[PDB]
Length: 534
Ligand SMILES: *[C@@H]1O[C@H](CO)[C@@H](O[C@@H]2O[C@H](CO)[C@@H](O)[C@H](O)[C@H]2NC(C)=O)[C@H](O)[C@H]1NC(C)=O
Ligand SMILES: *[P@@](=O)(CCCCCC)O[C@@H]1C[C@H](C)CC[C@H]1C(C)C
Ligand SMILES: *[C@@H]1O[C@H](CO)[C@@H](O)[C@H](O)[C@H]1NC(C)=O
Ligand SMILES: [Ca+2]
Ligand SMILES: [Ca+2]
Image (cartoon, rainbow, N blue to C red):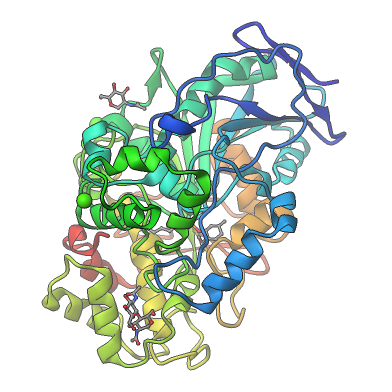
């Protein structure tokens, strides 16, 4: 029933879901299989003429979150679940996974010129797919608001398949393949979105967690040049939890170790060209070898095995430096956080209970940090359980004497204070920032990492006012205030500015506040950012 005519003249059919029209599973690239593994995506050249696109394709290969070279119960358990026929039926994954999904309000026709919201999912750069992020809530609210938008989502390679690094990967020019998948999807939207009723000049990119750090990377891509065929690929960005990635170069120390580990795992330790050896192994051996490297929930936690790393080609340098040096695209941005970003990651080191163990955990995580810097950090984030995350809970959530401590640190470096650093240095366009405390009181996790996905795609709550409405007004008008909320969202100029600069959210609704908390942690972490890179 729904129909579109692509740039190359092909004409496809979608599905009419009543409350919206969807075109799911459109291939935007050749399958990154065989000798195309770990390499840049190749544009799709073939025919889609007369084809039906009524369901999401398989996600790219997934990594066991509890994977690691060690053997243990959670690793065993998740593997048991992940390799099950039931799981593989309900959630199919494949190396041939580079597809794109377009969903629009019902009745939309070519030429409508609706603003476009291109979603980039977050899954710790190791798991994830588009099928788990329902656009219906967004789309519907946009219609109700009288600001209809088109929701676009793109699959990208994760874990070893999309973020392998090391000397060989650098030499070949194959770094950050997963980010390149994302970049091609954008180019595809530029060329084809008009056929669906969207305006290619009104694209707002947005993601959460890894999707968010992805949006930052796109702003920094090619020293800030975001054009394609002479026109910008997007006019704005919304980052939900995540700014710059605190990572060393692709041919760095941990990028090289992981590469080597993965190679030994696949049986390529003796190969003179391990990379070629890796392209030759079956998908099973590769999937297996990857699950034997640390997953995000493993003890390594935030020190991810796979993630965006400066390559000196498309991301020319340390991401913090690029921001200080003004090498970014000049676009208006909304960037916010959840009050308790680190409680999730803090669950991965619950066998650390004494300050002596805490100091060593940090030392193993941040190899570039001197004992002096470790000491300063452990002074800014003290053992006092009342001072940690879940913030403001007193002596509760004391799973261990160090849990709340470790959570306060990880969530700040990885997201919360990382954001403030971007904000204090960024002059590309108007900035807007928010902080959620919607789930205050939730035992153990607090207003935890990713709860925004729930209030943006699944359930309604005070938070949906920002996650849907405000995000919609911004994509349409480049100002979240056009949404018509009762609380005006003030512009963010600096964390040292007088007056409220953050939009806040609690169980009841919205209010304004200041971005001046944990200043001591900020200087401990960012006085010399590279001391804390992974
Ligand atoms: C907490 O548990 C981790 C995970 O097992 C311990 O780290 C591993 O320890 C073994 C030896 O027991 C090493 O061979 C592994 O390489 C370690 N894994 C990692 C990912 O580093 C860690 O020592 C324990 N921490 C505390 C404070 O007891
Ligand atoms: P993000 O993708 C975590 C990014 C880690 C950065 C370290 C430098 O968070 C995920 C988001 C999804 C929706 C749910 C799980 C959550 C984590 C991977 C635990
Ligand atoms: C990466 O950088 C090179 C050199 O600047 C450029 O030609 C290439 O197009 C860039 N890649 C992407 C995906 O933009
Ligand atoms: Ca090596
Ligand atoms: Ca500039």
